[PDB]
Image (tube, coloured by chain):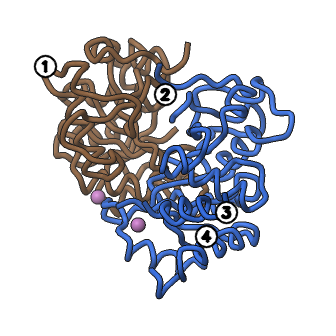
Chain colours: A blue, B brown
Amino acid sequence: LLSSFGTPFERVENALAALREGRGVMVLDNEGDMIFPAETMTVEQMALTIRHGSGIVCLCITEDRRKQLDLPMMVEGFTVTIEAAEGVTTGVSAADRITTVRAAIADGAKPSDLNRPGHVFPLRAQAGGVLTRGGHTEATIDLMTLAGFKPAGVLCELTNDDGTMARAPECIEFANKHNMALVTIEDLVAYRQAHE
Amino acid sequence: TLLSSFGTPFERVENALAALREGRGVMVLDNEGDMIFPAETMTVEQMALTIRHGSGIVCLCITEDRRKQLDLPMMVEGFTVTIEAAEGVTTGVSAADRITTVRAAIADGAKPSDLNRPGHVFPLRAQAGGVLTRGGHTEATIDLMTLAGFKPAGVLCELTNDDGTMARAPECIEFANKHNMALVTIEDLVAYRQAH
Ligand SMILES: [Au+]
Ligand SMILES: [Au+]
């Protein structure tokens, strides 16, 4: 961990740089999630998440963004699911999922820009980020805001081919193979605490 | 032809019923090809398969009666709100967890309390009348399960290439041949039903 990616603070900083550079980040909590900036995620990165991830690809958003899109919570942090109103076909391909993410996060996006339900799963982050709730959703948003992006990111859980969820060592190995950075939620909490 | 390889249309349906009764999957084409399995026989390894080469949005096709029995609202005013087995799982995302959730939902005597919401399994409520009412993969699934002698509950997932594109028709055939699945089209099924 320390050997592969550096001290906690270095892991954080390294993760911001990777994000800004267009690389992904593995975020570990048991469960490691591949994460990317919603604004820059590519089609290829989407394809990788479907292939190596659970395929339940989530769009982490803020409450403001949720309100702006008029997306209710699924049950009285998943909201109701979405699909781009324009520019997609079945909504399932990597390209279509990207199209939907881009539509949701666009500046000036309106509710009508999205149909519901759909194949992209928004997650509303708790205000306060990881200082409030140590979830991958929060970590995603914190990482994006610290990196300098809009506070919206895409995440997916890393899954082994046999269907078991990747363990730390597998997550390290995958990050290495894919030139992603890797950081833990505790690291992030620590970092924010320090720079308070 | 590639499709004739599987027989004539009615042969294709019958072969599909045979494959299902044997616990094998069926590739249902409409291009979008979905892998399907009876919910009663689907295994962990089949589930791992669906996550690895499918979209990872693995759906449980159910009837309105079953949706009512589980007290599952539609997600929006055919997806219902998502589900998780209330017992027997952890994060809900692994292949074993998803299969656990499927089995919980379909059990004889299943109760709403047997599932938590939201979750990582996506029930889809089939239109009454099946493919004669709506030629969707959801209806196709339910029709095939019923015709095969199972409970009207099956699991489906769209076949995706590693590069994120949805499998094309010939790609679906290749995958079916590789995994010993039967192959049929929604049209074949419609025709079969109309005949009978
Ligand atoms: Au991990
Ligand atoms: Au298989």
Report if the beta carbon of the residue with label 3 is closer than 8 angstroms to ligand 1: no
The disc numbered 4 marks a residue on which chain? A
> Which label belongs to residue A195?
3
Relative to B5, is A111 above or below?
Answer: above
Q: Name the residue type under label 3.
A: His
Where does residue B90 sit, x and y in percent of width and height?
27, 47
Number of the front mark, 3 or 1? 3
Report if the beta carbon of the residue with label 1 is closer than 8 angstroms to ligand 2: no
Residue that badge 2 annotates: B136
Task: Report how far apart the C-alphas of labels 4 and 1 lie in the structure.
Answer: 49 Å
Residue drawn at x 33%, y 26% is B142
Q: Name the residue type under label 2.
A: Gly
Residue that badge 1 annotates: B109
Task: Report how far apart the C-alphas of labels 3 and 1 lie in the structure.
Answer: 54 Å
* Front position in the image: A155 or A160: A155
| Extreme residue toward the left, this view | B108
User: Which quarter of the figure has residue B66?
Assistant: top left
Where does residue B126 sit, x and y in percent of width and height?
40, 20
Specify whether B24 is left or right of A148: left
**Image-quarter location of ligand 2:** bottom left
Specify whether A130 is left or right of B189: right
Task: Report how far apart the C-alphas of labels 2 and 4 lie in the structure.
Answer: 46 Å
